[PDB]
Amino acid sequence: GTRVLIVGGSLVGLSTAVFLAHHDVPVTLVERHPGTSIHPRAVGYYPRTAELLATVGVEAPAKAAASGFEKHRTRAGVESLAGEVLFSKEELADLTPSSLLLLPQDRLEPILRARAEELGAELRFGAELRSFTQDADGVSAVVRDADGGESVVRADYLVAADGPRSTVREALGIGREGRGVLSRHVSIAFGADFAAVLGERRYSVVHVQNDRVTGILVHDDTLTEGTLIVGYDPEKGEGLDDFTDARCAELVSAAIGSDDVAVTIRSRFPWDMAELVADAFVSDRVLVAGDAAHQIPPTGGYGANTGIADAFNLSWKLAHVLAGTAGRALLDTYDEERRPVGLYTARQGSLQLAVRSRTATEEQREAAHDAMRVTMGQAYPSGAFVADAGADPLPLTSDPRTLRGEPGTRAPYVVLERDGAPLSTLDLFGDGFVLLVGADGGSWAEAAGEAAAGLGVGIAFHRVAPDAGEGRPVDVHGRWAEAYGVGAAGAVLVRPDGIVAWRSRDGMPGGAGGRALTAALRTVLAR
Ligand SMILES: Cc1cc2nc3c(=O)[nH]c(=O)nc-3n(C[C@H](O)[C@H](O)[C@H](O)COP(=O)(O)OP(=O)(O)OC[C@H]3O[C@@H](n4cnc5c(N)ncnc54)[C@H](O)[C@@H]3O)c2cc1C
Ligand SMILES: COc1cc(=O)c2c(=O)c3c(c(=O)c=2c1=O)=C(O)[C@]1(O)c2c(cc4cc(C)oc(=O)c4c2O)CC[C@]1(O)C=3O
């Protein structure tokens, strides 16, 4: 009945549901909580992440849900929101059609929830994975519902999106490396009349510091929902269980600094700033994604972004394995591609935490990469692609403006037109294998036909040429070939996740194009 089980219906579990259901994979997701968390959590989604979301219709609604917060331009440090202000302060179109999506997770998640439900994913909230076993043939998972009733869900594969304390990762005996837990915090979600204390003021985030509370205070677009994130010191013997609703009300009220503002605590969650990365992201039929794979220090919001990229990477791979078009070893490439990225990003988070706390060495500041290089400039060291002979390999990240369609990299953004209507290379990707070809590369259509037929996998052919053709992509400014690092007679095979899989810099005479592409694609699909 149900073929991929996801554990966790936070960001990554749901990005997984949307991506698997996009690819016509039967998904059951389980989330122990009765819905998606009202806490804001990770608030910035970088252009690359937005592009990923574009492929499943999530960018436009998320951009719409984000304009409410676009006004929230001011960062400040205060004694209390009602008290004294101590301090207050206030991509680009050749690379990406997307901008930074300033949207809290509690707004992005319901969008992903809706889209997953539309694409036919089964989402069981208030449902807890107790334990699981895996054999040669699949995975058997014990689910306890809200009523306390248990059942065994049978799946081909299990995706662990169950967060930092992932009982799956632990059940599998996958350890973790990194600098570990830096600080322990509690997120306190509450309802309050922010307007009555804000006036015309709108903040992104407020640092609160007075005798009774230190912490990070956020308000939503509506000025009704707020979060207070506070430290606790286990050296003082403080823990989570000290954050009783009494205690939570007292902190929030001292952060507001009013008394007259009625506060309703909705929930507190524990939240650690940590650098901890799984040794392995794949254990036979279990795929570890998200905070379960990589706790990342939150400065730059790399965690939530990395985890959606995890979900995007593994999703089509599972779809290809489940449909018998890819060898089971295709999934191993999830680990090969995303673990180095996971580990690199987690360390990037630590550099940023160090640069922001003003405790970085010039070496930490030297090694800290632009967020666009971290999220868009990735060159997978190895995985589901075929490298170019002779062309020197890329490091893990580069300036994404220097990338020219090297296999293992984001197939570049090239502005096109179809019947006068704007488009890009990116609009072409996300649904299946895409073969793109230059002006002189008309023969590569037969090439795509042969490989598609030979291997039983769809290959959407598009020639990119600088003069019209009704319903044909027009290379408006004649950039495609240069941008993809091929001649006008060349071809570039793009994976479902928009990563370049293979290319021919030159044309291939006769059947050679078809034989080569078949072998290229046979390798990427582990066949
Ligand atoms: C309170 C809090 C505040 C945060 N604040 C920030 C922030 O300010 N900045 C930032 O960059 N990141 C922040 N994060 C982290 C961010 O939310 C994650 O990086 C992002 O959501 C990716 O995590 P994930 O979806 O993989 O896992 P998580 O977000 O941890 O979600 C894991 C989910 O798995 C579920 N689960 C666990 N065990 C089971 C089980 N047995 N059965 C079913 N479901 C299970 C949990 O209930 C949870 O919903 C915060 C997280 C929390 C919890
Ligand atoms: C020592 O110095 C620090 C240490 C930290 O450990 C730290 C930290 O951990 C931070 C943080 C910090 O400033 C610091 C910080 O100074 C925030 O600034 C933060 O990014 C943030 C939040 C919400 C929003 C909402 C909106 C719309 O837009 C934002 O711009 C926005 C955010 O940007 C919620 C908290 C946040 O995610 C975060 O975790």
Image (tube, rainbow, N blue to C red):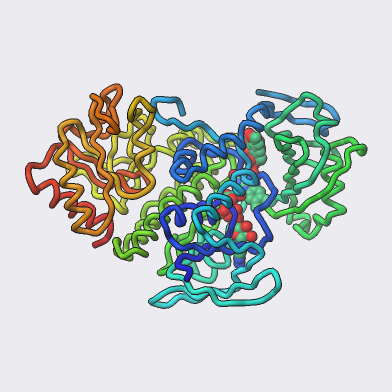
Q: Residue visible at 46% across and 65% down?
A: 4
Q: Residue visible at 27% across and 26% down?
A: 479
Left or right: 450, with 107 as reference point: left
The image shows residue 52, relative to residue 416, as above or below, that is below
Left or right: 86, with 258 as reference point: left
Residue 334 image offset from top left, x and y in percent: 39, 56
Residue at the outermost left position = 510
Residue 51 image offset from top left, x and y in percent: 45, 39
The image shows residue 308, relative to residue 486, as above or below, that is below
Rendering quarter of residue 80:
top right
Residue 11 image offset from top left, x and y in percent: 57, 51
Number of marks = 0
Closer to the camera in the image, 4 or 219? 4
- Residue 178 in view, yes or no: no
Rendering quarter of residue 320:
bottom left
Image quadrant of ligand 1 equals: bottom right
Q: Residue visible at 46% across and 40% down?
A: 54
- Residue 315 in view, yes or no: yes
Closer to the camera in the image, 462 or 341? 462
Left or right: 252, with 282 as reference point: right
Residue 464 image offset from top left, x and y in percent: 25, 32
